[PDB]
Image (cartoon, rainbow over all chains, first blue to last red; front, side, top):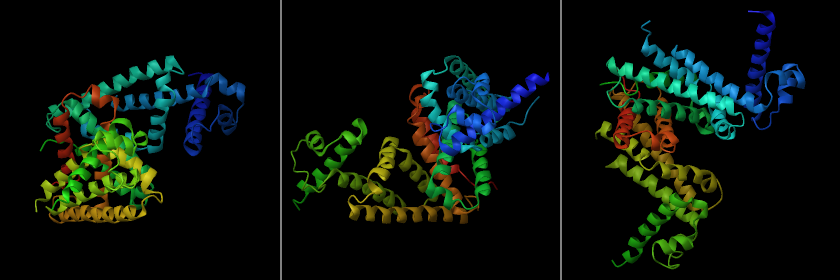
Length: 197
Length: 195
């Protein structure tokens, strides 16, 4: 684990953590590589050693999301607890969720960075298979109703999507007085959704 | 009472404006095109609808009155299910109405109808809150603030409508009518108390 590489990776990560933060505070189309560099304490030449364009930063953030999801699914693990962790992971960062929805149009569906996008789709396919495997196992264990597994997949997607929209609604955030009470209620809903009667 | 040369026609004007709105996008549809699809000239501008905005508001007002009629018609579970069915049928109309919130409702257009829309939406909000409170009191729903259940119903419906607009749904999901009733089961079962 040489020092040179540990410290290259650590800077790379600060670049990414800083870019996301700037993207979410100011709107991604404002933010340049240059501002991300100034935010981190480094210059043009240095940031280009890690990312040659904002688009590579964009895709790398989404790849890291997909790798984080992959790591959550990676022994007879507790599938109920994994279901809860899956919803918590998905609803943790609603701003990032919403950013990724726009990045889907602005860079994924254009292959501005074609090698990274090709990779993104393959890990997504694997995460899709991992999530539906969890579904099939909860069905086989009698927890989930025995309907096509994509029914539960689509339910989960819908719940996460509207939960994120709920958090972006001016009307909704004020009615939501106890926000962590509600969050845990939402997790319970997700784990319990489509449970066999 | 012979009044209904007007009645019949009005419902046909609305039914056809909406269809055109959803097929071609509302910004592109004119009263001219609506009188055309229905088979009339401009016996539509005295047919109520002194403008398209009045058609827009009428459609939203009709939607909220039908929602109101749902709550009026004893079986709280069957009513909960009818509510989700009502909200999730026609996701395209749900999306039109969302755009009209910004394009029409939150402006000075047709203020008398917007005022009425705000009132009956508050009415319907209170009837939903009340059904929730009853289901909590009757032990069916978990005893947390009613707005927990209300926000959760809003999120399910909203995410459902987006799902119905998604590349996934219309190309890989096979059994759409079974899925629909599965999603309504989920809404009815959301937040139920476990004994």
